[PDB]
Image 1 (spheres, rainbow, N blue to C red):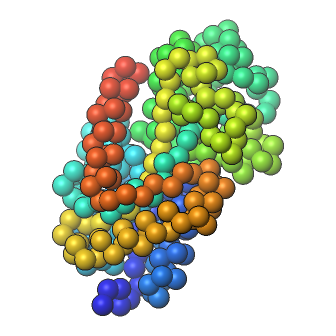
Image 2: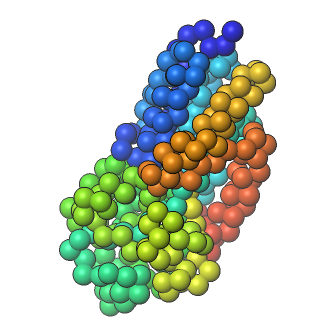
Length: 299
Ligand SMILES: O=C(O)CCCC(=O)C(=O)O
């Protein structure tokens, strides 16, 4: 009979970031399919640790899910000593929603138009400039620290509570540049409020096919990306996980769903619950190496 009443999707960041943008798309589609409201609960704090600690404790009845992030599943262990939950044991996978490029951008008043211009400008002014971090341990955060190690540039991190307040400060010039998820940055690109330099992925993003990759623009072998999930509390009934996976997978694999995701700067995910588990395990192992190379660890 599930669902017989309202379902909550817990989202670990405020609105105007990529996590909430994908959650709203999913919530609308699930609501229509099942005839019950799927509502969003924006529960910010500690790079998603407060949200994840909460969902780890709720009843495993199918009326609460987590919209997971690389932090919650893989990277927060690199910057936080204690987290309030154990991502390996406390959840059961549902599906990977999307794989998403990150984007290097600068504030308009910084007089640089390419990755090579940025590296020169910063090498001339070591330890003077500032960059925006959407959250401690985010793929943006670790992407910039890897870029720093691979190019020799010295620039100072300023953490924020999500992409939304960070990007407001980048538009004002209170930070000079960022690497962060494409969907959140794209409306600012299109309003001309920030200047895009390059994508972080191994291949160009086709709908912005004339922005180069960081690797082709001067940093050989550089590759990073972000991603987003639906997770359930340990013990959620198999029938419920399977139904929810099937419904989301149908949306993501549809022509119309693929178009909707790509228009906002995201590639559809899809696959099985165990495919999500494989992606999480690979990412744990790959980011732990990046963190060591870049000199990042928990205080
Ligand atoms: O790439 C990541 O680690 C996810 C960062 C998500 C975010 O900052 C937001 O939704 O506001």
